[PDB]
Amino acid sequence: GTSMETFDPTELPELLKLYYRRLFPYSQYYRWLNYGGVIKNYFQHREFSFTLKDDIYIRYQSFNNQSDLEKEMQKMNPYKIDIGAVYSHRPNQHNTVKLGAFQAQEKELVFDIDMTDYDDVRRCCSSADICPKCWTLMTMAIRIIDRALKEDFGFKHRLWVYSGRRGVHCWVCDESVRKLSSAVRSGIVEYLSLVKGGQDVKKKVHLSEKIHPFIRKSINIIKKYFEEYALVNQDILENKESWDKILALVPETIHDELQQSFQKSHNSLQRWEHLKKVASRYQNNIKNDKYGPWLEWEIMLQYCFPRLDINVSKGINHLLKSPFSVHPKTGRISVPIDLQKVDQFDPFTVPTISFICRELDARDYKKTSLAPYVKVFEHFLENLDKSRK
Ligand SMILES: [Zn+2]
Image 1 (cartoon, rainbow, N blue to C red):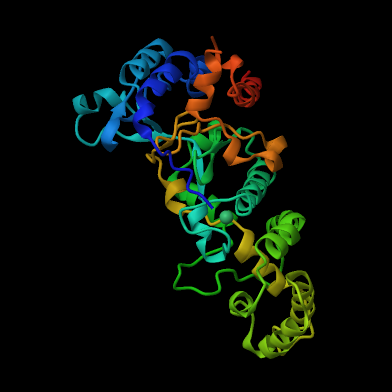
Image 2: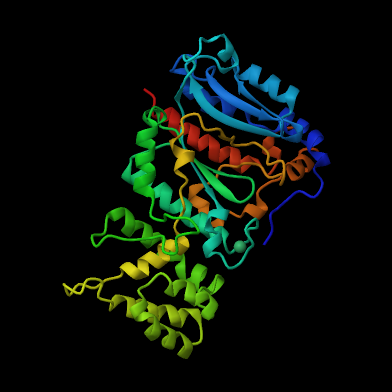
């Protein structure tokens, strides 16, 4: 695959200047972080962090209103913009605050799903690269996590954003969610988590006998993709070097039976069908006479289910890349992802700052390929607006 790295980043300053002057959607961005103006000082107490040239960054930047933010962004033309928590005081006054009183109080619940966490189950790309094959992992992650957040937790205001390179972020923005404690956020991650363990750990998925609906519904999403993704594109049972990795996920007592059936068959599709049958006949507990799909599902989960960094989601003060910021090393915009078109999302066609600046002079983002992504954002804002009395 490819890491999408910009070959010549010396173009970035003049492109950023144009982007921040004419294309960055300031009015919509402020409408987001002002949250209807119904909490006093909510925008003014938000931390922003700007990264400049040479990875030099400034923390605890804050702004009075939309005009202020516009002017500072156009003055500093940052390479990166990170959004942090809403604080007890204006961040840009935190040094006037007596020690201990400056506290992060609220922030969106965020997830950060990164392709490198799947390195142990990708056959297509080296660690730093992505390709059209492994991007399906992100498609599944979005569907699995968005459905749970929406249906199981009742979170209504969920913004999925491209990372600009190798992953996706989710911003959960409900007012009740912004107030949740670190402990509660950790509990949400634990509910959503099924793949656990480092490279130290060979088998990373262990299912209980009793199936919770979250596991069933997640498996059912994976099943829509698994044949094309895992058996065709990844070809996970192509040969012994690869199918041995799967046998390491199932009891040793069925390896020989599976080894021999893998050698008699000719493709990953056939070999998966044998695995499902042998697995469904394994007696997990010599006591009872109960059989089922747990091994099959554990394999599918280990290969297809997202890995969730609990630190990202539990920290109230965590800085995360801003929607509509520019990835300095790829040029790609951190665009919102239309959930209704998740299967059509291609990171390789996400607008770059170079591309949309060329479109601009050939007035407004509506003249450019950024426009449909602003409309996705606007729908998210409309749903937030509808929720307020
Ligand atoms: Zn790949």
